[PDB]
Image (cartoon, protein in one colour):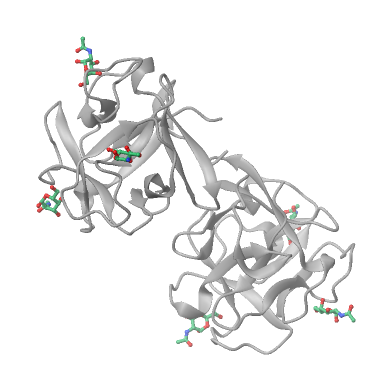
Length: 150
Length: 150
Ligand SMILES: CC(=O)N[C@@H]1[C@@H](O)[C@@H](O)[C@@H](CO)O[C@@H]1O
Ligand SMILES: CC(=O)N[C@@H]1[C@@H](O)[C@@H](O)[C@@H](CO)O[C@@H]1O
Ligand SMILES: CC(=O)N[C@@H]1[C@@H](O)[C@@H](O)[C@@H](CO)O[C@@H]1O
Ligand SMILES: CC(=O)N[C@@H]1[C@@H](O)[C@@H](O)[C@@H](CO)O[C@@H]1O
Ligand SMILES: CC(=O)N[C@@H]1[C@@H](O)[C@@H](O)[C@@H](CO)O[C@@H]1O
Ligand SMILES: CC(=O)N[C@H]1[C@@H](O)[C@@H](O)[C@@H](CO)O[C@@H]1O
């Protein structure tokens, strides 16, 4: 099961549960932060071809739009939650370098900066540009891309 | 280990070894053809993250640029060959729906038609357009996409 870091391409910061817990509470926000440690490692659980659950490795909780909205509007915050259902399905587009939700919007840093400060929230947004690009890299070498689908 | 059909998206035809043999000779051309059977099933052997070998399931031979050059020119024919080496590396881009060789060109039907006739050759070409799109589908449901990387 590949373990990887979700690296914001423009800044080199990574996706974290806010606070960096090895067992974040349900609805903990997902933020960007420069630190690397085992509590910001992720896995991907395939459900249906490209679609699956982005899983926080330390806790097992997965990435949700807050409230579990089926078609989340722009600026809906991303959180971790233990529930599994179809409204938490994403795809890890390692060719265009983005993360897309089942209803078609992407994970962004809130406000869309190419250099978001530590603790910047992540949100859903439909726009496509350099500041929403992410790559999926080895915990052993933050420049080495790894295949999240195996 | 997923077995799949390589489906030309605009026409619905599939990638075949010319002649449909369970053991095509080395340098057998890869063509498009409407038929479905076990001698046009493929598998994908991952080598390095997105890069891997496109493997003819019945024979074990893989897709090569004819002549095995590292940086083949436009209109280089695609063939099957037993050899394994780094000039036979491709990625299966199931987000943009194409097949890309390590040096950057794509698999095309020769001449670029959206509805090529049976037996049309495939070739490498750098252009991107609707007639070089491919999707990767179940041998049991040719309209169901399947994940080729697992
Ligand atoms: C000291 C410590 O554990 N720090 C972590 C930090 O590494 C990062 O995970 C951050 C994300 O909100 O949360 C915590 O502050
Ligand atoms: C009952 C219900 O809708 N539960 C969901 C839960 O499954 C998860 O999606 C969460 C994310 O914030 O939002 C909701 O509370
Ligand atoms: C115009 C502008 O600044 N747009 C970006 C938008 O593209 C998206 O990244 C969003 C995420 O919160 O933040 C900004 O609004
Ligand atoms: C008998 C017959 O037509 N069978 C096959 C056909 O199914 C297809 O694989 C084709 C590819 O060139 O090769 C043969 O014509
Ligand atoms: C060693 C050798 O024969 N060289 C290559 C072979 O490995 C394969 O790439 C082939 C494809 O047409 O082209 C060449 O013949
Ligand atoms: C639709 C079209 O005009 N296609 C071009 C190239 O883009 C390429 O497809 C090539 C492959 O042989 O055939 C044509 O020259």
